[PDB]
Amino acid sequence: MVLSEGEWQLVLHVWAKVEADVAGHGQDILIRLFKSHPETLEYFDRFKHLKTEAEMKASEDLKKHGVTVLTALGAILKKKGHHEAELKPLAQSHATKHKIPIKYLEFISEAIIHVLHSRHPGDFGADAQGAMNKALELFRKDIAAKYKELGYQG
Ligand code: HEM
Image (cartoon, rainbow, N blue to C red; front, side, top):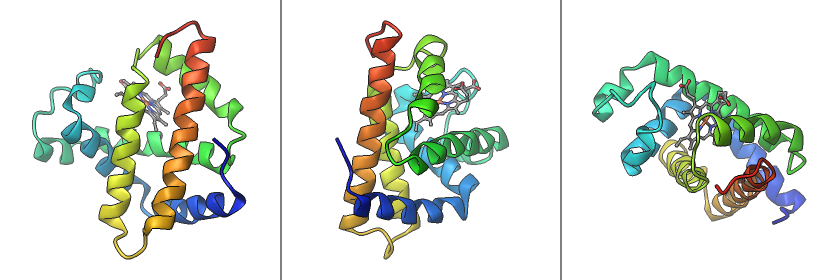
């Protein structure tokens, strides 16, 4: 929906923690996604040979993709909602090439929140959680708009 300026400030303050260790966050987020929602792994021809968490933790290539994911998300979040320019290519690849259902963006949003609780206990309270959830919900809703514009049902 629309975040307050206060809420965006909180979102970006938590993001600065992500930016201090991008690869470790990105690795944790993709592995959490694959553990909580294994169906999502099946969509990655690149990774689906990885069978266990331990195997996933040992893939440098998974870590690299985690950086790529978070770099993109970060650019989006820094736009504080004014992210049309960022969402157009992302929606195009994800709807038309990777063919990812929108529901999976809910799953990755859940993984992000989980990893923030795991990595930043004592520094990720109800206020920050609420703000980040709003930002991720806006992102998902706006990607779903872009899927529809491409002619899909996400
Ligand atoms: C925060 C949410 C996400 C962001 C920011 C994101 C971002 C990216 C970026 C930047 C790329 C590389 C460029 C491109 O192809 O667009 C990518 C590739 C990809 N994404 Fe995502 N992604 C997200 C969620 C998801 C989810 C939830 C899935 C599947 C369940 C998914 C599946 C893929 C696949 C399959 C590729 C190609 C990977 C490869 O073979 O190299 N993405 N994503």
